Image (spheres, coloured by chain):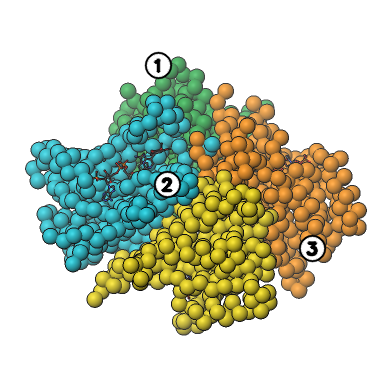
Chain colours: A yellow, B orange, C green, D cyan
Amino acid sequence: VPVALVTGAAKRLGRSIAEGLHAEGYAVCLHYHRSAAEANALSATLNARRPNSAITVQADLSNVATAPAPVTLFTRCAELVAACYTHWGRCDVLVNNASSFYPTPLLRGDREAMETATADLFGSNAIAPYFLIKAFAHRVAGTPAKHRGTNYSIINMVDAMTNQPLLGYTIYTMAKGALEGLTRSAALELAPLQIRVNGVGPGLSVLVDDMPPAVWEGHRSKVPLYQRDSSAAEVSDVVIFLCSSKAKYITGTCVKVDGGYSLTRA
Amino acid sequence: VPVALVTGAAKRLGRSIAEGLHAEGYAVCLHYHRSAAEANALSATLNARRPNSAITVQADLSNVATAAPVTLFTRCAELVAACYTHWGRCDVLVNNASSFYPTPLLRREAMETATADLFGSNAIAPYFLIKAFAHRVAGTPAKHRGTNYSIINMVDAMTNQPLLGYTIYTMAKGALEGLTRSAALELAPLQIRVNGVGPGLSVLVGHRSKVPLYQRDSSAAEVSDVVIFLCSSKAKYITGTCVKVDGGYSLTRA
Amino acid sequence: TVPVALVTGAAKRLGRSIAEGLHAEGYAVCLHYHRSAAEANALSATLNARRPNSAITVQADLSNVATAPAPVTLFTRCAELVAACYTHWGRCDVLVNNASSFYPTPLLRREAMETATADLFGSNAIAPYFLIKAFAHRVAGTPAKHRGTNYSIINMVDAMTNQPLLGYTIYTMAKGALEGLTRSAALELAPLQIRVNGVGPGLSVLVGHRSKVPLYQRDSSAAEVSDVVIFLCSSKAKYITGTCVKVDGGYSLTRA
Amino acid sequence: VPVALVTGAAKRLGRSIAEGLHAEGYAVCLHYHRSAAEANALSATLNARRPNSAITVQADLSNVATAPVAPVTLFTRCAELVAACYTHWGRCDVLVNNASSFYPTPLLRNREAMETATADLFGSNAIAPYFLIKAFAHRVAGTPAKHRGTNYSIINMVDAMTNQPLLGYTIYTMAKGALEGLTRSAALELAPLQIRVNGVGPGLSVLVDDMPPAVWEGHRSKVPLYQRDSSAAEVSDVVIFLCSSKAKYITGTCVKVDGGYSLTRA
Ligand SMILES: NC(=O)C1=CN([C@@H]2O[C@H](COP(=O)(O)OP(=O)(O)OC[C@H]3O[C@@H](n4cnc5c(N)ncnc54)[C@H](OP(=O)(O)O)[C@@H]3O)[C@@H](O)[C@H]2O)C=CC1
Ligand SMILES: NC(=O)C1=CN([C@@H]2O[C@H](COP(=O)(O)OP(=O)(O)OC[C@H]3O[C@@H](n4cnc5c(N)ncnc54)[C@H](OP(=O)(O)O)[C@@H]3O)[C@@H](O)[C@H]2O)C=CC1
Ligand SMILES: NC(=O)C1=CN([C@@H]2O[C@H](COP(=O)(O)OP(=O)(O)OC[C@H]3O[C@@H](n4cnc5c(N)ncnc54)[C@H](OP(=O)(O)O)[C@@H]3O)[C@@H](O)[C@H]2O)C=CC1
Ligand SMILES: NC(=O)C1=CN([C@@H]2O[C@H](COP(=O)(O)OP(=O)(O)OC[C@H]3O[C@@H](n4cnc5c(N)ncnc54)[C@H](OP(=O)(O)O)[C@@H]3O)[C@@H](O)[C@H]2O)C=CC1
Ligand SMILES: COc1cc(Cc2cnc(N)nc2N)cc(OC)c1OC
Ligand SMILES: COc1cc(Cc2cnc(N)nc2N)cc(OC)c1OC
C-alpha cells in the first residue's frame, strides 16, 4: 500500500489531487494549515470508502519559528514526513501543493504586512518544499535497499503563467521561480535513488468568483481552449499520471496544464 | 470507435505508439515509407486481435514531387483522406515519421535531397497533415464531430543542446515546436489540441551512461505511454505544450 | 584594417539601420536586396559618398526555388553572395541574416501554397543556413595567419514567436528553425571563433496595437534594434554566442 | 553626472562592473560585506581618477536582523543602501544586484548550518535584490517628474547554467530562479516609470582554482568558444551596454554571457 503526502490538501486542487491518488490505491496524508473542518471532512469520506486510508496533519509552512523553545520550519517539515512513516511505515509520493497567493506591489504597525508576507509566500511556495524534499530523500536513503518502494515520485505545483507575470505579485512569482529551480536540482541529485521530481503548472483553475460576474467571465474568456478556467480534475489527473509507473522515465520537467493561456499576448 | 493516424508507424517508437492507441480501442492507420514488410506484419497482429482495426498507407514525406507530378501536400491530404474513406473519421494525428542523419557545416544535390528529406519529414509534412486534419474536422457538421481531437508532434528534448553536425535536423525540430504552438492557438476554437512529446535517448541502435535517471536509454513504451495519456480525455485541458521524456538528460552539461 | 559585413535585405527599415550602424563602426558593407533596387542603390551612394569604396549592392531571391541559367539553386545563389564580399574586398567578417518574408498562411477557411512555403521558409531559414555554411567554408579555407579577429553572425529572429501571431504558422515555424540554426551553428563554429547569435524584435517601425507594449507604449525605432546588432558584433561581446536577445520593450511579458 | 549602486563591488565581476560604469562617467556607490580593504582601495583609485566619483557602504544582505548602533531588518538595511546614493549625490540611476553567496547545500549523503545558509543564500541572491528594487522604485516615484533622470536601469546578475543545475547547489539554484522571476516581474511593473530591468547570466567567469590543475582545466575545456572561463570585462562590458541609452528598448530579458556552455550535454 503506497503512501502519498499532499500539502494543502483540504480543498480545491489539493483535494482533487488527494482524491485522485486515493482512487489509485494510495493511503493519503492530508496536510492543512487553517482548513481543519474541510480536511477532517475529506479524511472521513476517504476512510469510509477504505478503512485506514487517510490521516490529517496541521502545519504552518511559513518561514517562521513556532511556539514551544521555538520550533523551526525545517523541524515542522520533517514532522510531516515522519507522520507518514509512523502511521504507515512508508512515504512514496510528495505533492508540494500548499501556497499563499496575494499581491506584494513594488509601488505604493506596518512592517507586519512586510516581513510576514515574505516568509509566508516564500516559505509555503519554496523553502518548505525544499525542506520537505530533503526530509523525504533522507528517509528513502535511510531505508535499506531491500525495503524501498518501487515508484518514488515528487510533484511540485508551479505556475504556467509566471513567464508573463501577474502585475503586483512579485514575491509569489519569485517564489514559483525558486520552485521550478528546486524541481530541476532535486531531479538531478535524487536520480540515483530513483526519486523522480517533476512539476505541474496550472494556468487558470477553479477561478475564485469573489468579483463582478462580468470581470470573472473576462478572465476565463482569455483562455484560447474552451474559453474557461479548468476544473480541478483537469489538473489533478495530470499529477496522478506523472506519479504512475507509466511515467517512470519523466523527471526534471514542468508540464503546463493551461489550455494555451501561455501562448497569448496583450 | 475513434481513429488514429500514426506516421512512420512501422517500427520502434511509431510502432509502440500505434500499439498503445490500439490498446485503448482506437482503429489505427499505420503509415510507412520503406518498411512495407514490418508495417504489414503489425497490421496483421492488430487486425487479428480486433477485426478491421488497422490499415497501412505508403508515402514519401520528403518535400519533393513523386509518381502529372504529385506534390507533398497532395500526398499528405491522401493520408488523412484514407482515414475518412475507410472509417469515416480521424480523431488523432501523431507526426512521428522522421529522418535523422548529419548535415555538417564544415568539411551538391546530395544536400538538396537531404534538405527536403529532413525538413519535409520533420516539419513540412506535419504542417500539411495538420492542415488537412483541421480542414476535415471543420468540414464535418458540428453534431457529427468527435469529442476528443488530439494531435501529437514528436519533437526532441535535446535540441536546446544540439547534437554536433545535425543542423538541418535540429532546425527541423525547432520548426515542429513552432508548429505545435501556432496550431494549438489557431485550432483551439475547434477543440483540437496540439502538443509535443520530446524523447531524449530512446531504444538506441556509450553516452547512455550519462542519463541521470537509470543511466540508460528509454524503452519505446516509456515514451509511447506519454503520447497515449496526452490523447486521453483526462488531458483535455493540455494544449500547446511540450513534454520531455528524457530521464533528466537535458539537465546535464559537459 | 577595414572589416566586411554582408547584410541581407539591407535596402530599408531594419536592414538599412543595421547596415548604416555597421558602416559607422568602420565596416565595408555588402548590401543585399531582392526587389528594392532603387533604395539599395541610393543607400550605397550615401555610404560610398561618406567613405569611398565602403559599399556595394547585390541582388538575389532567397526563396527556396531554382532560377533559370541547368537551373541556379538557392545554395549557389547564397554562395555567390558570400563570394561577392571576397571578390571585392578579400574578406567577410560579419553576416546578418535579416531578409524575411512575412504574410499569413492560415490553417482554416495551390500555386501560392507551394510558393509561400519556399518563400517564407527559404528567406527566414534555408537561405540563412546556406549563407552560414558558405561563410564558414571561406573562413575555414583562409590560412590561420590571414583570418580576421572578430567573426560574427547575427540572425534576425522574433521575440513574440512563443506567443504566435494567429494565422502566421509557416513564418512562425521558419523563425523557430532560425533559432535552432543559431544554437547549432554557434556550437559547431566555436572552434573557428565564429560567434552566432540572435536578435529578436517585438514591434519595430510599423506601417492601438503598440499601446500594449509595457515600455513607452509604442513600437521601437530601427536604431533601437540595430544598435543591439552592432554591439553583439563588437569585440566587447566576444564571449557571447548561441544566445537570443529580445529587443521588445517587455511585449513578451504580456498576456491576453 | 548619473549614479550607480553596485552590490558586492569590492572585487572580481562586481569591481569590473563598477570600473566599467565609472569609465562611462558614472559616480559609483561601491557596496561590500566583508571586503573592506579591497573596497576602499577601489574607491581610492576611482576618486583619484575623478574627484568625488566613489563612496562605500557596508552591509550584510543576508535575510537576518542585525544589531543596531530593536534590531535592524534586511529591508531597512537595503533602503539605507539606496538612501546613501541620494544623500551623497541626490540621485540613483543604475542598480546592479551582483552580491552573491555560492556554496553547496546537499540534499543527500548526510543544524546551525542548515539555518544560516538559507537566509544567506536566499537573501543575497533574491530577497535583498527584491527590497533594493522596491527602494529604488519608490525613490524614482517620489522624485517629481521634472527632476527625474532619463535612463533608469537595473541589472540582476543571474546564471546561464541554472537550467542545467550544479549538483548539490539547490538553494543557490533556487535563489537564482527567484532572481530571474524578479527581473520579469519588476520589468513589467516598473515600465510606466521607464525603469528597465534586465538580467546578465555568466557561465564560467574567473574560475576559482582550489583544486588540482587537471580538474580546473577539465571544467575550462568544456566551454565551446575558446575552451576557457571568461574575463571579468567580457561580462561587465555587457552589463555596461545594457545600461547605455542605446539599449533603452530592452527590458525583462536575460542575456547569457557563457561562450556556449549552456549548449553542451554530458
Ligand atoms: N488555481 C490556479 O488558477 C493556479 C494554481 N497554481 C498552483 O496550484 C497549486 C494549487 O492551486 P489552488 O488549489 O488554487 O491553491 P490555493 O490557493 O487554494 O491554496 C492551496 C492551499 O495552500 C495552503 N496554504 C497557503 N498558505 C500556507 C502556508 N503558509 N502554510 C501551509 N499551507 C498554506 C492552504 O491550506 P489551508 O486552507 O489549510 O490553510 C490552501 O488551501 C498551488 O500551489 C498554486 O500555486 C498555479 C497557477 C494557477
Ligand atoms: N529515438 C530517439 O532516441 C529519439 C527520437 N526522437 C523523435 O522521436 C520520433 C520517433 O523516434 P524513432 O522511433 O527513433 O524514429 P526513427 O528514426 O526509427 O524513424 C521513424 C520512421 O520515420 C519514417 N521516415 C523516415 N524518413 C521518412 C520520409 N522521408 N518520409 C516518410 N517517412 C519517413 C521511417 O519509416 P519507414 O521505415 O517506413 O521508412 C522510420 O521508421 C522521431 O520523430 C524522432 O525525431 C527525438 C529524439 C530522440
Ligand atoms: N519589424 C518588426 O516589427 C519585426 C521584425 N522581425 C524581424 O526583423 C527582421 C527585419 O525586420 P523588418 O525590417 O521589418 O523586415 P521587412 O519586413 O521590411 O523585410 C526585410 C527585407 O527582406 C527582404 N525579403 C523578403 N522576402 C525575400 C525573399 N524572398 N528573398 C530575398 N529577400 C527577401 C525584402 O527586401 P526587398 O525589399 O529588396 O525585396 C525586405 O525589404 C526580419 O527578419 C523580421 O523577421 C521580427 C519581429 C518583428
Ligand atoms: N563567476 C562565475 O563563474 C559566475 C558568476 N555568477 C554570478 O555573477 C555574479 C558575480 O560573480 P562573482 O564575481 O564570481 O561573485 P563572487 O562569488 O566573488 O561574490 C560577489 C560578492 O558578493 C558578496 N556577498 C556574498 N554573500 C553576501 C552576503 N551575504 N551579503 C552581502 N554580500 C555578499 C561578497 O562581497 P564581500 O567580499 O564584501 O563579502 C562577494 O565578493 C554573482 O551574482 C554570481 O552569482 C553566475 C554564474 C557564474
Ligand atoms: C489573470 O488574472 C488573474 C489570474 C488569477 C489566477 C491565479 C494565478 N495564480 C494562482 N496561484 N492562483 C490563481 N487563482 C488570479 C487573479 O487574481 C484573483 C487574477 O487577477 C489579477
Ligand atoms: C562546474 O563546476 C563548478 C562551476 C563553478 C562556476 C560558478 C557557478 N556559479 C557561481 N556563482 N560561481 C561560479 N564560479 C564553480 C565551481 O566551483 C565551486 C564549480 O565546481 C568545481
Q: What residue does disc 3 label?
A: B2
Q: Which one is in front, D3 or B18? A: B18
Query: What is the total number of numbered labels drawn onto the structure image?
Result: 3
x, y (%) of residue C120? Answer: 58, 46
x, y (%) of residue D29? Answer: 18, 49
Query: Residue, x 45% and y 57% (percent of image)?
Result: A130
How much space separates mark 3 and mark 1, taking CA atoms?
A: 66 Å
Q: What residue does disc 1 label?
A: C145
Query: Residue, x 57% and y 52% (percent of image)?
Result: A143
- Report whether mark 2 lies on the same chain as mark 3: no
Cβ–Cβ under 8 Å for marks 3 and 1: no
Under mark 1, the amino acid is: Lys
Q: Quadrant of residue B233?
A: bottom right
Q: What residue does disc 2 label?
A: D169
Query: Residue, x 54% and y 73% (percent of image)?
Result: A56
How much space separates mark 1 and mark 2, taking CA atoms?
A: 44 Å
Mark 2, ligand 6, within 8 Å: the answer is: yes
Q: Label 1 is found on which chain of the structure?
A: C
| C31 left or right, relative to D98 | right
Query: Residue, x 46% and y 31% (percent of image)?
Result: D222
In the image, residue C43 sits, relative to residue A189, either above or below, namely above
